[PDB]
Image (cartoon, rainbow over the protein chains, first blue to last red):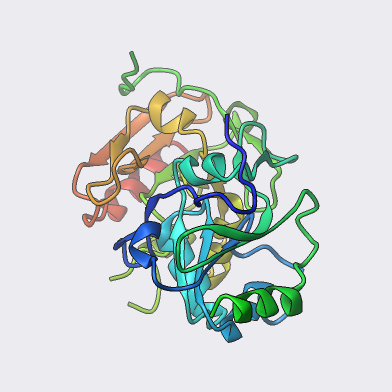
Length: 151
Length: 151
């Protein structure tokens, strides 16, 4: 089964972005990468989604959800997200990162937990945060300090 | 396997709407129903999606796609769709209606063909249109005349 720990090589993957362009994690070696998993585009709470808090991060942020690319494109534009948003539509990556759960109101609907992984220039996992509660937000300040140490 | 023909009882199903409320086709017996399958919310071409052409139909229109409810809710609101939009997220219904295909740019992504079924007050299929080409639009005028004959 899948378990991701600090110090391990981050599991590689290739997913389509909002323009259906294939994005491969390992092609980003040489750059700090932040994986930002979210349960669902257009989750309602506010004028802008919390994913916009990654706009200011000094790294290559990959937002990842199981939403289809067409909807993620509208979500990206509506919320002025300035970074790549990927669609894990077959749930390959939520499984590889062990961040899958079933949405309570939708039997058999598997989606990402709210999670963040920071990956160094060598492709190793250097920070991990996974919340079972989808409404919690990650500690952005700590994440940015980790990114700084890897830059 | 599944095949839907004129004169048959429409296959029953229960799917969540944009508020995650379960909607069951057979509960609509006594009313004319129009199933309007579409491949994907937020498909770009125009200021408003063609699904809005069902706003004027004198029947209970159920829009159906494999998009998740949260995205379909944003799609419904953006395009001022006045009718129920259902999420066939496990592809149960596209299979039952034999309107599934794989999106060319996304391996393993199964979605609805552009299709319309009109169902009479007894729950029987009375009109069927299925387009392999997702950009074609159905003959709205004929559909509305069929609806009239069933009213």
